[PDB]
Amino acid sequence: TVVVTTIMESPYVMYKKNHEMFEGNDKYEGYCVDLASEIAKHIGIKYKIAIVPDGKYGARDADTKIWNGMVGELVYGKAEIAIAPLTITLVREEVIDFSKPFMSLGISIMIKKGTPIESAEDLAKQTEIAYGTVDSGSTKEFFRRSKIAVYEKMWTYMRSAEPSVFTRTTAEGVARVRKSKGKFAFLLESTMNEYTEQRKPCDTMKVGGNLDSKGYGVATPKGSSLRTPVNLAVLKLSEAGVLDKLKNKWWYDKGEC
Amino acid sequence: TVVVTTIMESPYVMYKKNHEMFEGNDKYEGYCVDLASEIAKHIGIKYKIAIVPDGKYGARDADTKIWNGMVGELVYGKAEIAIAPLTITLVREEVIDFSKPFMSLGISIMIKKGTPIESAEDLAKQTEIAYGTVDSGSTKEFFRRSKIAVYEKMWTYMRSAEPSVFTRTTAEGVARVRKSKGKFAFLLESTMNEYTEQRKPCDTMKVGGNLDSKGYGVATPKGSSLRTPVNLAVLKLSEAGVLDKLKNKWWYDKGEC
Ligand SMILES: C=C(C)[C@H]1CN[C@H](C(=O)O)[C@H]1CC(=O)O
Ligand SMILES: C=C(C)[C@H]1CN[C@H](C(=O)O)[C@H]1CC(=O)O
C-alpha cells in the first residue's frame, strides 16, 4: 500500500456527509480524491489517503531548514505521493519531483459583486479597498519576489497593512470578501476563484486576467520508482479527457449559481 | 558547445532580414531563439542552433519504428536539447524528457472574419464549411484518439474529406482560411491562433473556448545531465516573469492589428 498525502481544500478533498459511517479513503470525496483513484488505477497500486498532519502545503523554514506540509511528508519519507492543488514552484521542484500539470492556472482577483475593481492595476492605485492573499503560500511569494512595478506596489501595501491582510486559508479569505461590504479583495488562484464563483450565495466573481501562469503537479520524493508511472498517468488522463471531465464535474456540474 | 535542435515556425524561430549577413545563431530571431538564449544563460552553456533537417516535430513511424523530427534528433543523439513549440504528449514523454511547460495552450478554432462558426459543436453539425488541422501532429492525434462524440464526428469528417483537409504547415492552413472566402476553418493551437490574429491583414480570429489543455516543453534525451538544469531554468524564467515578457513581445508588442 502506498501512502498518499493530501490536504482538506474544497473542492479537491472534502469530508463526506457523516464520514464517520465511512472507512478509510471512502471518507473523503473531491477532485483529488477522484484524481488519486484514477492514477492508482493507471499505475496499479493500493493506496491510503493520509491528511497532512500540519495542514500545510510545503515551505522550508528559514532558520531550522525543515520542510513542512505535504512537501515535508515526501522529503522525510512519511508519504510516497502528494495529490493536491499543490503549485509547481522552483524551490519545491528542487526537493521533490512534480509530474506534468494536471491543472493549469494563474493568480486571480476575487471581488464581492459591485466592487469597482477590474484589475491588479485598479487595486494598486488605491487604498480604500483592502486586498491580500492566503498566508505562506505561492501567491504571497509571487508578490514577495515580484520585480514588476504594479505587483511590487501591491506587495509593499500588503506587507505593511494593519490589520493583517493575509489569511490562514482560502475559505477565510473568501469569508472576508463576502463579509467586508466591498472593502476587501482577495488574491487567490484562478481555480479556487472559479470554484467560489459557482457557490451560494453567488456574491463573488473573478475579475480581469491572470497575473501569471502555472500549474498543479502530483508530487513524489526524489528517487521514487513511482515518478515516471505517475507522470505518464497524468498525461494519459489529460489526453483521455479525464482531467477536463473531473474539473467540469466538481466546479460546474456541482455548481450552485 | 551544446546542439540545440529547433524548427522554422513563426514567431518562435524565423529568418532575420538577410540572415546571410549574419552568422550562426545570429541568423535567427524569435520566441524560442530568445528562450534558448535565456536558458543557456541560466545553465551556463555554449550552444548552436541546428534546424531539424527533416522539418518535423516528432512522430514514430508505425512500420520502421524510427522517430523523426526534433524528437528524433534527441533520441538518436544528434542534438542535446529541443527548444520549439513542441507539444507535451505521452508518446513523446515515453522517449524523451520534457521540462515543465514554458507555454500553456489548447486546441482552438481559426476562422475568417464573418464565418458563422463559434464552436467545435458549430463545425460538426454542418458540412458547408470545411475544416481541418495541420497534418501529422498533436492536434490531428487529439481528434484521431478522441472518444468525445463531437470530436469523433469531427475526426470522421476530416479523415474522409476530399480534397484533403490536412495541411503540411500552420502557414498553409492559415493561407487556406484567408483564401477560402469563409469555406475553410482551421484547427490549430491557441498560441499560433492568437499570433495570426495579430498579423496583417487581420482577416482572422479565434472563436470559442479551447478543446483541451496542454503545454510546450523543452526536450532533452533520456539520461541527459542537462535535464534538471533545463527544468529549473524554465521554472526560474516563468517565475521571474520572463516567459510572459517574451510572449507579450513576440505576439502583441510586434502585433500589427
Ligand atoms: C490553498 C493554498 C494555501 C495553496 C494551494 N496552492 C498554493 C500553493 O501551493 O502554495 C496555495 C494558494 C496560494 O498561495 O494562493
Ligand atoms: C506546427 C506544428 C505542426 C506542431 C507544433 N506543435 C504541435 C506538435 O508538437 O505536434 C503541432 C501543432 C498541431 O499539431 O496542431
Image: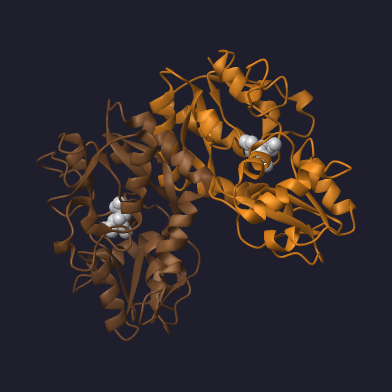
Chain colours: A orange, B brown
Quadrant of residue A120 in the image? bottom right
**Furthest-front residue in view?**
B21
Where is residue A23 shown, x and y percent of the image? 70, 21
* Residue A110: x %, y % from top left: 73, 55
Which residue occupies the foreground of this view, B63 or B208?
B208
Q: Is residue B248 left or right of residue A74?
A: left
Percent of width and height locating residue B20: 14, 63
Residue at horizontal 27 percent and vertical 28 percent from the top:
B224
Which quadrant of the render holds ligand 1? top right
Question: Is B96 or A49 nearer to us in this picture?
Answer: B96
Residue B2 image-quadrant placement: top left
Whole-percent x and y of residue A138?
A: 63, 38
Q: Is A42 displayed left or right of A245 in the figure?
A: left
Question: Where, by quadrant of the figure, is residue B94 drawn?
Answer: top left
Seen at 50% across and 29% down, the residue is A93
Residue B147 visible somewhere in the drawing: yes
Number of numbered discs present?
Answer: 0
The correct choice, above or below, for B169 with respect to B126 in the image is: above
Q: Quadrant of the N terminus of chain B?
A: top left
Which quadrant holds the C terminus of chain B?
A: bottom left
Position of residue A185 relative to residue B159, above or below, is: above
Judge left or right: residue B77 versus residue A197. Answer: left
Q: Is residue B128 above or below residue A212?
A: below
Q: Please name the residue shown 63% across and 17% down the image.
A: A65
Q: Which residue is found at the position 16% from the left and 45% from the top?
A: B68
Q: Residue pushed farthest left?
A: B64
Comparing B184 with B28, the one in front is B28
* Closer-to-camera residue (A215/B89): A215
Residue A37: tell me if it is visible.
no
